[PDB]
Amino acid sequence: WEQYRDRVNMLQQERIRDSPLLQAAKENDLRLLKILLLNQSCDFQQRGAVGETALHVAALYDNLEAATLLMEAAPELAKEPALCEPFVGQTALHIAVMNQNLNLVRALLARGASVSARATGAAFRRSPHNLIYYGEHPLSFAACVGSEEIVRLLIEHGADIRAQDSLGNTVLHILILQPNKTFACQMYNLLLSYDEHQSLELVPNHQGLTPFKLAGVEGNTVMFQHLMQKRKHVQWTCGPLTSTLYDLTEIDSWGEELSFLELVVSSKKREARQILEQTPVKELVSFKWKKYGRPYFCVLASLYILYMICFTTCCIYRPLKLRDDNRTDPRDITILQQKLLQEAYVTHQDNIRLVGELVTVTGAVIILLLEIPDIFRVGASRYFGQTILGGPFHVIIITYASLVLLTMVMRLTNMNGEVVPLSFALVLGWCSVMYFARGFQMLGPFTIMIQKMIFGDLMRFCWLMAVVILGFASAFHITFQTEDPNNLGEFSDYPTALFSTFELFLTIIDGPANYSVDLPFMYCITYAAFAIIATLLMLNLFIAMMGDTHWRVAQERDELWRAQVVATTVMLERKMPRFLWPRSGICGYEYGLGDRWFLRVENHHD
Amino acid sequence: WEQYRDRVNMLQQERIRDSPLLQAAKENDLRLLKILLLNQSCDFQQRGAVGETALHVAALYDNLEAATLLMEAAPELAKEPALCEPFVGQTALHIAVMNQNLNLVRALLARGASVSARATGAAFRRSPHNLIYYGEHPLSFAACVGSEEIVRLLIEHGADIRAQDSLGNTVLHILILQPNKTFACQMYNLLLSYDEHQSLELVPNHQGLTPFKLAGVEGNTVMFQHLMQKRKHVQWTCGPLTSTLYDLTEIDSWGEELSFLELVVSSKKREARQILEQTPVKELVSFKWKKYGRPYFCVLASLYILYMICFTTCCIYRPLKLRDDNRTDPRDITILQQKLLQEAYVTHQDNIRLVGELVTVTGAVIILLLEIPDIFRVGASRYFGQTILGGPFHVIIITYASLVLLTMVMRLTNMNGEVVPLSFALVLGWCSVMYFARGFQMLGPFTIMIQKMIFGDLMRFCWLMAVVILGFASAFHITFQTEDPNNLGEFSDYPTALFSTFELFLTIIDGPANYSVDLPFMYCITYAAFAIIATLLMLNLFIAMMGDTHWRVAQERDELWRAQVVATTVMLERKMPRFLWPRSGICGYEYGLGDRWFLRVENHHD
């Protein structure tokens, strides 16, 4: 981690100190080099405890002339890579190219440096510990620094361009996965022009992505539009409006298992949804939503709503009988107990209940069999934690399916307590009905906002109801355990004391007040303190902070709804059969450029 | 104060009026000087009732030529300082240097002015009455005005640079304690270059601060970064990212009693926390919080929370017995009285209560013995009033410790009434659990905000509940003291009338309404007026004003949380023993610049 790298760099500078040749390479004394390379008895493979050579030290400090004296002294010093643990394959050519030193890279290439050296150490692998990820070929280093003359010089003596890293990423993948500059686009055009002809544009990595798909996933909209300029084809410019024929071979991907749309909307990176605002794909996903996705989603929502009315009606009509044993007990009310299963179904209305309960359990197993391969296909933490893919709605529909299957289990095996899974099944399924509210323009963004307020604001005052109401319910319990709980049984015992203080803390019950009897003077001052620092201070501060966080979230919230409609369009596709979703676009074997399906857009510009 | 200075300046101008020589020095008549200095019988030590000399008057109005005629008349006039009460040591050299008059300071230095004159009056001491604090040496005046040629001229004829004021501040301290300019930095470099070698950089004042520490305390981030440029040491610039080896001798201060971090975060000045955003100290305190401060704080959170569950459980299980004397009284309920101490502990569960009560009282004395030297070390008003150091949380934990010790006292001495200290002990300790909630990213800033809303907004409507509900409870008491309290005992008597109007003013109880009987016509119109100007007007205006003050406070609130995590990092350090906190950084005896501990940072720039 950080301290290990600090220890490595400290040991590196210690080994710069104790060896005088590395000191002379550092400070450019220009005397001690001549004596310590004038002799020929000792081999000049002097390395540090880190493992770098002296030519690495000469390249490291932009020291050209001293490095010319070392390459005069030994030609083989550019040949060997460093034997370090973080720098396990870094040669002096890498330091030469990444410092953009022209005479140094010319001289090192003239003496015969290794043009293909895989620097596969931990300090050069893609990691959040490293500030940059530039690959490990010198070609990738020259491509990342943007210097066109150096990468031209490296191509003109070798450096095959389709060389990959340990992650399978080619050099164009490393051009994608960068902070965006205006200096990385025209030299990407240079690298595409040097391809000279399977191609470099369509090579995948070990992650399974094309450079186009990595442009989609990583949120690079500039290179997305710039590479869209190659696939596009204009038609005519008859007037101010022009026509444009975009290509959807790698966008829609009708014959591919991993669709590009599923990779762009289900991305961990935040910027990928901005690619959803670009005109070659926004019009495609809007046409797919308007023509097909919205009415099939409305039919699916209506079928789910009628299924939930059927489950609720079969839930209210649960079989009950009168309580056989007498109560003989105050502070205890039950009047209706649950019938046994063998005596449950004896009437015609029991069969009417039974057919709808079978519809309920078959709807549950359809939900389970439809959702379980989506857990087993997508990464499960990525499937569950992402709010874009309906992750919370997926875990509450699976909790609903689990508790209704548990309800079926404890109905087949006669034992009391179906209220315990069944009430949670009712409330979780009816809160899972809000999953089908994202297809509507008015209901959807509010559902996004309540998902953000559940995931961001609810736990903050779960942990700040509890810290207040524990002490205040304990205070009310102490001031009221010396009194009669017959006339005021508000804080009679501790769980009802916490539950009463929780109710009154949200002001959903009246404060306890009795005027036929007297109350202790401790209760009045403790209750007054509770009414000050509980119901005036906290909830009005949520009015303030929920207003402020809604003002902060709303602008990206609307575009987040416009991303979840894309997710609903794609995930609602490829689950329903292929006959009911035709391939969108037009057949392209009439224009004159192949057999690839296209999308035509009208665009009235300035 | 202000009016005393007005009287001094009025008496000064009166003594300018009555003496014609000072008038001739003012308006440049160039005649009356020649007659009134042509004679030699009278000594020219004519001073005002304020006490300034005539050469002070000649320097005061940028009057060079008249001052040349006075120094031709008398050479000794530059020697004597003014004998004033506010200007007790101000010489004419001071007026010459602070007006930036080049020929005047050249002529006054040529005639032999006192280059070291301590002007230790009340008008030149550091005070909020004075608009400026420029020191009292002429060197400090030349240093404050920024004129490099004048301070060069003052050094070239004397003016030893390490001269201090009455507060012990040297000249570099006066360069720190200024409004920030771009004109005070390069001439601070000039004064550092004129130091020519213990040094002026490390000399302290009577307040005990280095110029670096005074740069930290006073909020001068520009000179902090500028003086950090001297301590820093780069390593290499291999690529776009560079390494930087900062020095932490005077920052972390492992061997110093008064740490620089404790002086910068516990500062009365607002701007000092902006120094907490600078990269040589932000990375250090973030590494100290992430590596060590956060898990020890979480272990302290778990220990304090389990201790409070133990105290609450031993509080609920308080020993009680049935009431021995009969009640014989309506409007009076008690059923359980407190047992005596000799009959309190007779069961095994009483021993289970007793061991947790001992854990409670030893936790109280650990809290007291841990916090009392922090009162006796830090300034007590500065320790108590500061929200950065957890001042309100400290006074509520000490109120908790005092009332639980009082509860132990009235348990050892048998007397009734443990509910009154014990309920406040419960609520104050459980509200003091929120002191440990600032180490989390989500809970912390909300705790900052509720601290600000107690300290700024809660008294504003303590004094505006009371002014409304006193008159309205009196109105309800007048309209309901002529009626039967059996049918409606809401406002039966005046303390219950105020408490009922206080409850209904926050709408935590229902309005009193009876329909089996009749209510007076006055109550309906008074209650309608209360419902208009009490629950619609006020509490919605706290919605509005709390939203507005949240939008004003939030931006500096988040950085205030990022400062209080620094305060918790430093204060949580040096209280636990030294073996649990290793010295942060790396040992610097391998680079080549000494035996001082360093901090290494990676910085990827543009």
Image (cartoon, coloured by chain):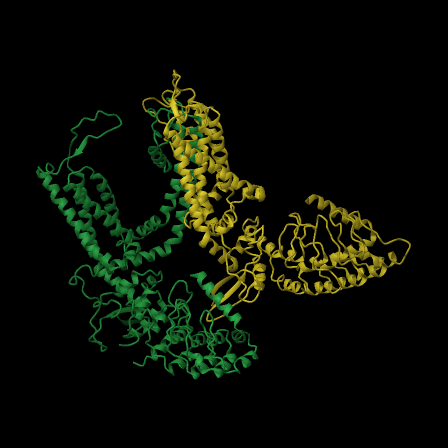
Chain colours: A green, B yellow
Q: Which residue ends up furthest to the front in the rendered image? A: A41
Compared with B518, A294 (above or below) is: below
The part of the image, by quadrant, that contains residue B503 is top left
The residue located at (24%, 48%) in the rendering is: A399
- Image location (x, y in percent) of residue A401: 21, 48
Q: Position of residue B179 (x, y in %)?
A: 61, 56
Q: Does any portion of residue B181 appear in the rendered image? A: yes
- Asked if residue B533 can be seen in this view, the reply is no
Which sits in the foreground, A538 or A109?
Answer: A109
Q: Residue furthest right?
A: B41
> In screen coordinates, is A116 left or right of A396?
right
Q: Is residue B280 above or below residue A235?
A: above
Q: Quadrant of residue A467?
A: top left
Q: Between residue A261 and residue A146, name the one nearer to us.
A: A146
Count of numbered tags? 0
Give the residue at x 63% y 61%: B184
- Counting from the top left corner in percent of width and height, residue A163 is at 33, 75
Q: Is residue B218 left or right of residue B508?
A: right
| Residue B477 lies in quadrant | top left
Percent x, y for residue A326? Answer: 18, 26
Quadrant placement of the N terminus of chain B: top right
Q: Nearer the viewer, residue B219 or B552?
A: B219
